[PDB]
Length: 151
Length: 151
DNA sequence: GCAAAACGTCGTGAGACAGTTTCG
DNA sequence: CGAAACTGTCTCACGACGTTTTGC
Image (tube, rainbow over all chains, first blue to last red):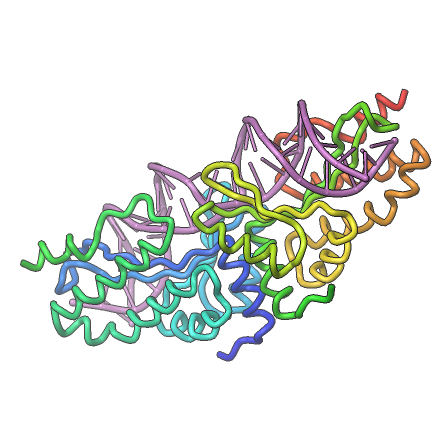
């Protein structure tokens, strides 16, 4: 899906404001390396303004909105559409462009990360960088925590 | 000054996110009708990201940045530059377009609001409308306050 | 007497994760 | 196995005012 540049310009400003580009390493025994590499693009807004997030679902054509009381979030996790979307959005980001670029990097490196523990750990390293670029305050699992479990 | 369109598209999204279009009636004795009609365009950001606000000062070409601890704000209150700015920004705003058009209306009517208490009140009613559109929760002075004083 | 700067603050509206679950 | 959803909440990073002082 090719997005309109005006939509992307406005949206990149909005994302730099209320948005969040997130990479997480989730402990999970069902994966071969006991952790899932999770990626999320999100936009949070007061629920009385969810109409704005509902429109995003329509305009971006993928993702959904979750309600959590007083605020709601537009969430996009599917890696394929995420890569497609972030690729077109990143040229216009000013505050979260580095995060976007790290996420695109991780996505493309995913297949290779599933094959090798050293690669996987390398990818986890880029997740650490995204978190350090964000206003990270409650992170727990890092590349360090993953190395210890692999060992 | 005329701003580039892509600049305004991005900024409108950033403003709809971290910005605030403010209208205030400030009790102050030195004014004929005992209140100042104050208008402010602002963008708030964590002080570590103060460079982005400083950059806005240069790109918008007027206004300034103030510090208040963990966060800083880009501030624009000069009525003429503010009017020129919002006129060009409002077409691209989505959550705060009404507030912006009401601020523009107030500015245009300031001259006549000065000559008549009743005009002053009507404009103060437009300030009520802006506060209602924002997520107002600590407002003290309203057009009802002024109505009482004007007696 | 008004515009504009300066300085101060309530109560969130966000951001940024964590943990667990679903099911092709 | 693993992509993606579902559910919770911590810690702010904002928004949106308010009061007081400048300066022409």
